[PDB]
Length: 402
Image (cartoon, rainbow, N blue to C red; front, side):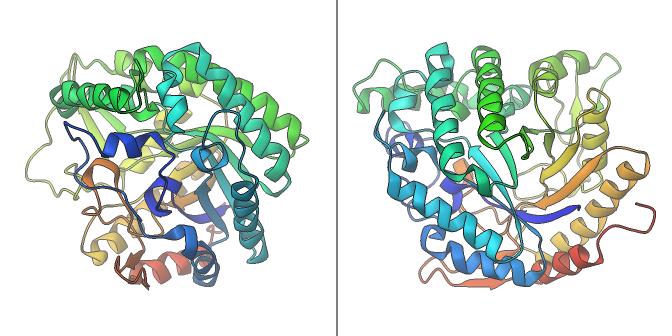
């Protein structure tokens, strides 16, 4: 049945991911990271409590990522302890009646992989595939739904914003500093790589990993990818919508796969060659883009205009210090999904970002996306009202129409 879940990503919640490329990036100059990820919210130790709490809130699905840097800290060196740890995670999700939604790659890579150029060179396809195979061999029988890559299209999507053009040389500088730090001519974390180079290479790696995963799970597990999708709206009559979609959406939607994971937060006003500034008058989130749950519908519709694949909402949420606003956002976001399904669009789940307040990459711990707050001295969890709220929406489930 329809999935009702919460989401997290390993690097943003687990803590201690020293083997991951973004750690090196975190500790060089110049600095693009506000704040070290460090311990995040210590979900490495608290994950089982989090799973029991999620089940208890009424969710039937649990999205999490497997951190490749734990499984393969050095090239060709496989951590059986990390594989067993993630198997305990999966079995804990199953034990509490939930469908595991597993992300194999969520922005970060092992240091050596970035140092070899990551996905900016086709040499990067082979290791990922092999990684996707190993985990599939060891854990595949417990997978519920599998996304190979989380938002590999983010670079192309945000290349239409002004921020990315302004910060770009600082990002490339910290890349070069990291490369020096690891004694390499290259350091290319996926989320810091050039989307124009990476997009076809990553797509190729996804289709190969797709075949391998389908093989290792006897074709019984949906395998796909997730992409960031705005509600893209024409901001001037000569909007570059066609070009932006070729840059950021269409190649990913057209790749082989069992579904498209739609991850939407807001709308974008698209000019001729770049996005337009935010319309002022309008409420923003901590991420400094408009508060807009209805955008979800647009996003879904957008994807449905260009594929017949089933759609999962693998991320949807709001960064705010005021949880009442998240309650309103959710009360408007779920009916948007329902509208899309009433028009025959095949949506198969709604997964909220995020379960916990966690480390929001460059912005640090500032942005509060979670249904559950965390004291980062004790790592105690305190559910916000929205947690039990969305829980009750999950129990209510689909309307009679659907």
